[PDB]
Image (cartoon, rainbow, N blue to C red; front, side, top):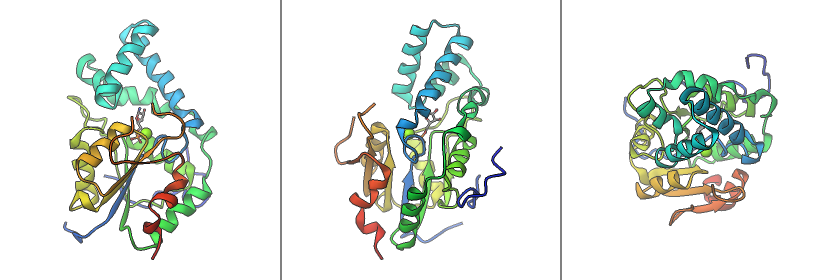
Length: 247
Ligand SMILES: [Mg+2]
């Protein structure tokens, strides 16, 4: 459990789960491989668990597990979306064996430079809300925020609802963006900024008319769409949207 964390940002201060100012400005943030580095190898651990699930639950050889995992991931943005639809997998049981079994407490540590950068972004007055927009389920999302010491830095969370049993609504699908817009109180896309490591997700935000979309590419792409700004480290946001950090 994480109830013994005492460092700043270790407590969630926004609500999980009525009009507002229309001129609202919102910066959306992906979480995985965004608020922490892809070199943490957390994504590798996730893929290991996911591939194990395909093998143990779908009785597939490792090579066929890779093919099916990649196929679903490519077209859906989440393998679990395909497992739900075609294999009648329960997404919450899956989630217990995958994201929720990661040894995060041994990997993620408070990220003070990230905390300070986000504080500066909140304090300029240029952005009204920092909103999390993740394909993870809420358990994992919250756990990452608390461990990284940034859980008080966001005004809300839009996560993929793994409780659904027909399909999952997730990035890069437009319905996921619509949900993020509604939940955050965002009136127009043109009042939104977005950072994500997924090229396809960035592609959707751009196509939808978001103001500025930043594609986070640490080393090599796992493709960057027309109109996106590329950085290799989230701490480079101050380099590329500098004005948002100034009063
Ligand atoms: Mg990601």
